[PDB]
Amino acid sequence: ELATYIEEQQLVLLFIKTENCGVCDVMLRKVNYVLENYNYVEKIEILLQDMFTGPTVLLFYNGKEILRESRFISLENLERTIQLFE
């Protein structure tokens, strides 16, 4: 909340996951893969405690939430959306 202002570094993607979650790990690999091709996206990972599994990806542009996907994650949607910022 204090470098959430430095979290206005253009296009940024939150990957949110939980401590015991098999898919999360796979999907993170999958997301990372896409992000190979797009240097101008910044990833932040948040690992929540177990105690909601996820994963959840949020995409923010200049702070505005532009995309939210969850549980099963259209890498197509993610990519095309990112692309709108070529």
Image: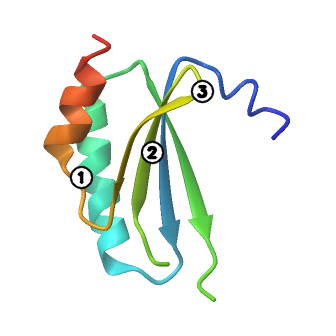
Q: Residue 30 shows which numbered tag?
A: 1
**Residue lying at the far right of the rendered structure:** 2
Q: Earlier in the sequence, mark 1 or mark 3?
A: 1
- The residue nearer to you, when weighing 39 against 55, is 55
- The residue nearer to you, when weighing 48 against 65, is 65
Tell me, yes or no, whether the two marked residues, 1 and 2, touch with CB atoms within 8 Å. Answer: no
Q: Secondary structure at mark 2?
A: strand
User: Which colour scheme appears in the figure?
Assistant: rainbow
Q: Earlier in the sequence, mark 3 or mark 2?
A: 2
Crowd band around label 3 with a 10 angstrom C-alpha radius: few (<14), some (14–19), many (20+):
some
Q: Residue 63 shows which numbered tag?
A: 3
Q: Secondary structure at mark 1?
A: helix
Residue at image position (51%, 74%) is 18
**Residue lying at the far bottom of the rendered structure:** 51
Please, is residue 51 above or below residue 69 in the view?
below
Q: Secondary structure at mark 3?
A: loop
Residue at image position (64%, 78%) is 49
Please, is residue 28 above or below residue 82 in the view?
below
Quadrant of the frame with the C terminus: top left
Q: Residue 58 shows which numbered tag?
A: 2
Q: Earlier in the sequence, mark 1 or mark 2?
A: 1
Position in image of residue 23 (x %, y %)? 29, 73
Front disc: 1 or 2: 2
Position in image of residue 83 (x %, y %)? 23, 20
| Marks 1/3: CA–CA distance | 24 Å
| Marks 1/2: CA–CA distance | 15 Å
Residue at image position (18%, 28%) is 80
